[PDB]
Amino acid sequence: PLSCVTRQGDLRLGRHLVPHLFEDHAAATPERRALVYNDRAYSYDQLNRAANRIANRLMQAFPELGTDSLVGVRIARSDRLALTVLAIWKIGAAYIPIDPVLPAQRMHDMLDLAGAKALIVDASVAAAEPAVAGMPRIVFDDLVMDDPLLEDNPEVHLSGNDLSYVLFTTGKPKGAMIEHIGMLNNIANKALDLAMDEDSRVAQNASMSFDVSVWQMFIALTKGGTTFVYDDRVVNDIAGLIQRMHTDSLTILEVVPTYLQALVEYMEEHPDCPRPAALTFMMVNGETVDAALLKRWFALCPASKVINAYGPTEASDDITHHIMSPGDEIVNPVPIGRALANFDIYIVDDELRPVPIGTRGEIVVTGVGVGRGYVGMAGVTAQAFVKSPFPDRYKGRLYRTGDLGAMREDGVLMFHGRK
Image (cartoon, rainbow, N blue to C red; front, side):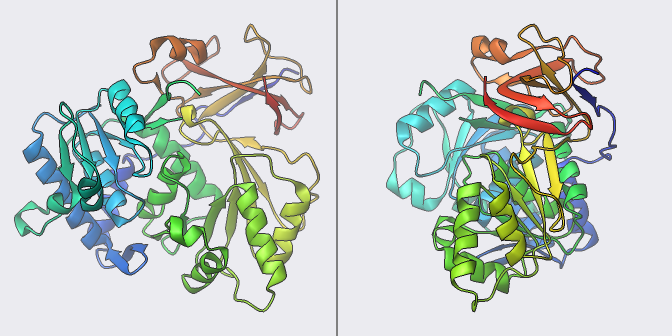
């Protein structure tokens, strides 16, 4: 057999994109708690009303913004960031996260490559830093001001093929273009594999420069649950984050292996302290995890399952999940797992021919989450985004990951480094 797994079409995604799923919950259960950021708690209705004020004032300021318009957002992770992104999406546009800690010349490159139409900052950034001629800048604090006349949903038409965000990753940065439907597919797969419901409590702990911060911020809002934003000050204090996850009764947490190690070490060294005993799932991603660390995690959090997650920013976050339970035979190397639904994955030679099961080759992927390429970089886009030679039910896109891997007889994928 050849190294092919096909899941295109496996998962119906429903009628509504991410912002609209949030709107559905705000209408159905306005008073449920939607988002917590330190001392600030928003109900669904409060979050929606504030996002709508922002959205409507953005359309007043920039009447031409809409489909595939790109808006930079230089706001630190917070309720303010979530609100601003939601507002941008509601008016049909897409955003670029530009962490305030990034230097200005990085911001310039990001906005120029993307052809961004405007930049939204908050008051602290505006006070620290000048606006740049040619790049309209507007301030969160003004956009979100009270006005009961500006609180209805914009009801701009959104299409799944429209951009939702451009995420940049030594050369000039490369801005991967992700569409609403790919973003939704990643969220839909995760909501199923993390057994989410309206009681889910999801950590938003990753840096906004990493694409995983997107599903972390919004997945709970598509399910009626709660996002807990854990900013850099909180995540940098391991003891404090653990105590927060305990007191928040957090259920879902994603980390990279070195941070997982810090959490595990702390709990082992402090067995007296409260633990994140409500966690149902810990997801690990970003770098290779080892079996012994996973087993140490399972000893500390026996009520949890773990998902090893892999995939490129270019395909809307992950393309495989490896779900593990405490009783499982967990050995090195840890698999990167099973294809997400609505993707096909192949291990191929340099000519894109699938190789026999067990042979190493390049991981390449087709399906609903393969994005558009790199904004303003047609050439580097052409190096990795090519027409699929395989059957396709979407837009015919293939992405070459530049990663080596191999496929097991059961279709489980293994990661073997960079090609």
